[PDB]
Image 1 (cartoon, rainbow, N blue to C red):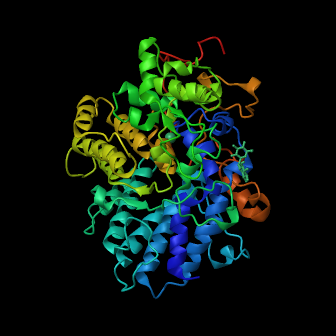
Image 2 (cartoon, rainbow, N blue to C red; image 1 turned 180 degrees about the vertical axis):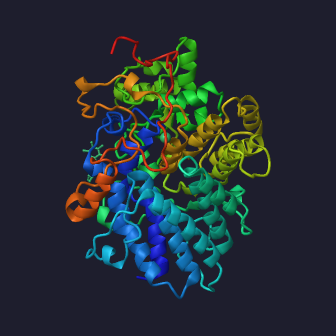
Image 3 (cartoon, protein in one colour; image 1 turned 90 degrees about the vertical axis):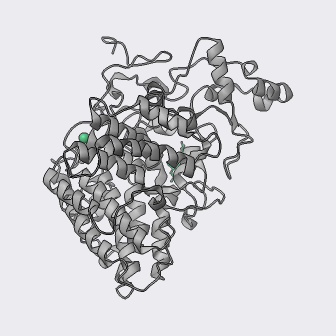
Amino acid sequence: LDPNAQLTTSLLQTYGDFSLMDTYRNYITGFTQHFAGGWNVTNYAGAVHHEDDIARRIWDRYYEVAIKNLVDAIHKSEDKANLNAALRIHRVYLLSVLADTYGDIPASEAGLGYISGISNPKYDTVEDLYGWFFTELDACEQQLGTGTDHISGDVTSMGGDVAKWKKYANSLRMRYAMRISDVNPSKGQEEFEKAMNHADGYIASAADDAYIKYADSPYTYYDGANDYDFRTNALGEILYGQDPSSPTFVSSTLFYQLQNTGDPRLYRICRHYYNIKRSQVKPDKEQNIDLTDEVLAYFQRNNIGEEPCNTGSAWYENWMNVADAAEFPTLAKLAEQDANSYDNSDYRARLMRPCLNIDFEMPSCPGILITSAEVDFLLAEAKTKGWNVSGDAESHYEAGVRASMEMLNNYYLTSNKISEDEINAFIANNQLGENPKQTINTQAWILHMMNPSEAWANMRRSDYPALLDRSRLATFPGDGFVYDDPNMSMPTRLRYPELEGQYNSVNYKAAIERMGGTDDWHKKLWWDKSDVNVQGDFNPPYGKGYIKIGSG
Ligand SMILES: OC[C@H]1O[C@@H](O[C@H]2[C@H](O)[C@@H](O)[C@H](O)O[C@@H]2CO)[C@H](O)[C@@H](O)[C@@H]1O
Ligand SMILES: [Mg+2]
């Protein structure tokens, strides 16, 4: 009821609501090809399988909680200009996620009547929404600091500092100006330069990174869905999984991007776990038994190597030979003590695959809004476009790579931090090269691994990184997965919630007619001009690659 408390709830929901995270585990982080091998991502993204109850969650949960709270608090804060501006900025942020997910969405008519359930809003067009983002963020950025009120509900890294909220608003303007740079290059350039030249500045260093701060509190997964306090980061929670036999595995797309470039992030992101006794309350190092070094030593002894799971395949598909516990001295000692716990062959099978480091799965992980590393990559790309940016593209790109590594050191890694020498060597071996747009946006995709909505939006916009071509990778109908969409390319949006067809029937129909007459998750959004690039060949040294030509 207090508008600062409504700001708090709406900020925390962003990453703190487990009941929308199935959309991120099952679809979006699979679409981006960061993760593959878990059952959930294989069944949904991996099979290009639409299910309304999964696809609808970002829409239903953000409109039911955050948008209702924000709209109510905005109406009730006209006397508190600083809070009012912060509420409106977070509303822009969430509406941009909603529009980048679904396309045309309720916004301009999503007011007091709509959140009370008595009014049907039209769906604003993506083009009109993006235009409004620029005017609203300009207005909010100037309104910040014209109040004397304390933004006491701020749970972000901005810590109620209006100067930091101003830099955040200008950085969002820069992101959205890049987003529209293919469909409207002149507006993109104008808006980008206006924001980057603004007297109040943008996020230029990690000290001004914008993220939501989450607490070290126990995980509860789907339990108590009615009573969510949103205090912990539910993205890392769902990636850890409610089921120890289905943790999140790193895809071959991400694995080979890292390995092929000598990226020191390879075995910071990827670890090998034997996790049968792991805590579900809070990921623990004691029983997420990290056997990475011993697994790599076994590979070296046997002239073999990693088999990261391909997009479309589960860990139990494209079966990788399972080493005996005797191959890993730590596990061998444990199994000689207690075979029921430590000689389980299913848990040893999952030990063979590269797993996401539990450092990315802890309750207190930050919820990234926008980082200085992203802004560095935006400046690098703007320079390559010929926009009026200070400093050469190489300098901005190198700043972005360095800041992406330091982000891991500062926000995630609890051990084995990436050294300055490792960063400098990686940068020296990975310059912009012949296709700077590809290099910049592939590095940004690594940066956005824990910010899946931005990863997916920027990949759709820039069409990089080149993904694995799903149509050239195996399917597994004999394993119970359903392949009901003959177009296997990565979806470019999600379908609208099907209940909208009843609950807001006229406006749902009109939005669907505008995209050509069916609710098509292969239809590109207004700012998405071209198809994402795909890798022309994939023949990994171990495991399975593209199916052999002519065998399909
Ligand atoms: O056990 C079946 C299935 O459950 C999935 O979680 C459900 C959850 O039980 C339900 O309360 C919620 O409303 O929906 C989610 C998503 O369907 C779980 O994610 C799956 O791993 C599991 O196969
Ligand atoms: Mg595209």
